[PDB]
Length: 212
Image (cartoon, rainbow, N blue to C red):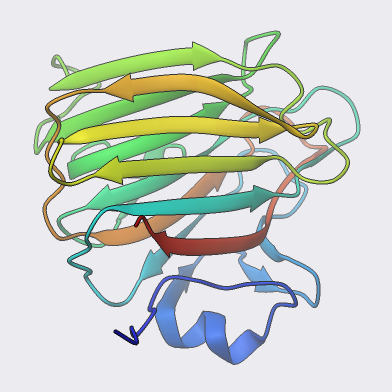
C-alpha cells in the first residue's frame, strides 16, 4: 500500500526533497517558503523537469501558486505531462514540439487569465492543429493572497481529465476532457514572464494524491 511519491513537495519546502525529484533549467531557486520559477525580468523563463517517469492510477495534482506582479502580470505558467522531459522553447518556456499534455495559465494579452489544455502528438502545434485544445477563463488567480491552487484530476478508467482552480476559497470549474489518454509521463513545470518586467512566477507546493 505504501507508495514512493516522486512528485510532491509540500509546505514547508525541504530543498533536498525538490532536488531529488526535479531537474532545474533556468533561474529556478528553492526558497524557504516557495520554489521560484522566474524572478522579475522581461522574457525570462524556466523549466523544472521531473526526473522519474510515473505510471499513475487515478490521481489528483494540486499546484499552489505564489505569483507576484507589481502591475498587470505578463507571461504564463505551464504544467506538463509528457512522454519525455521538457526542452526549452517559446511555449511558456518549453519547446513547441512534444508528446503529451500542456496545461497553461496565461496572463499575457488578456484581461482575465485564461487556462488552456493543449494535447500534442509530436507536431509543431504553432504551425499545425493540436490534437486537442480547450480553454476557460478564471478571475483572480494571482490576486488570491493565499495562493490559488491549480487542480489536475484524471480518472484512468473513464479516460477523463478535469481541470479546476481554487481561488479565494472557491473551487472553480474550468475544463473537462472526455476520452483522453495519459500514458506514463514526466511531470514538468514551466513559466515565462513574457513582456512584463515586474512579474515573478513561484510555486508554494505540489501535492500528488491518489484518487480513491
